[PDB]
Image (tube, rainbow over all chains, first blue to last red; front, side, top):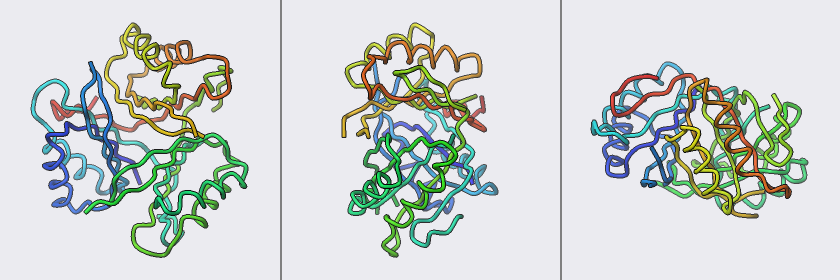
Length: 92
Length: 92
Length: 90
């Protein structure tokens, strides 16, 4: 699995959540953060996604979050050594 | 070294922290995030040495479980290096 | 690229931000978190390889007070970073 961390504009959050839902991504968390390069409000989404589907998930976010202006944000794809589901204790 | 990111139910937070402290886990940070029709969750971020990875994961898994959908997940992330600001000590 | 996650004292934040800016490290996000509880500020900064040490040093120098609880700096391997404005990788 990989961990996707995306920093997007607040005004694009609904488009992004919609695109993720249509791309079949359901499990995620998000929070408000302040960003720079004078700080601007941003929304940080964190999504665990298995390798075959990292590319499609990143694409949905890129398409939905873009405005074309400086300050659109970034998407980080981090490696994950192990992931566990707390409901069952199982390593996913 | 690893960076453990755990998403747990707020009502399980106290039990989780108690279990971590008993497992000799010490410094960590936490914040509230919205996750999935979203629900509030507590996101813990814990830096640990290799010998503490298993004990930390085990503690959260036993303490945060309710068996119902939405219990959360635990991500164990690789860390290239970590620095303690006070002492300037670096661990890899 | 690497992703740097730093936990610093709120009273040292402006000093940390100034030091980063001076080091040419401008793109980042931050948020308030609770530590150990005591409020802390968490910075998340994606940087190219040559900027890892300059970023770590800027924070180490500006955030230290000498008292226990000054924070930590994590350097994480990042596999890919995309610039949303262009839809391109970096």
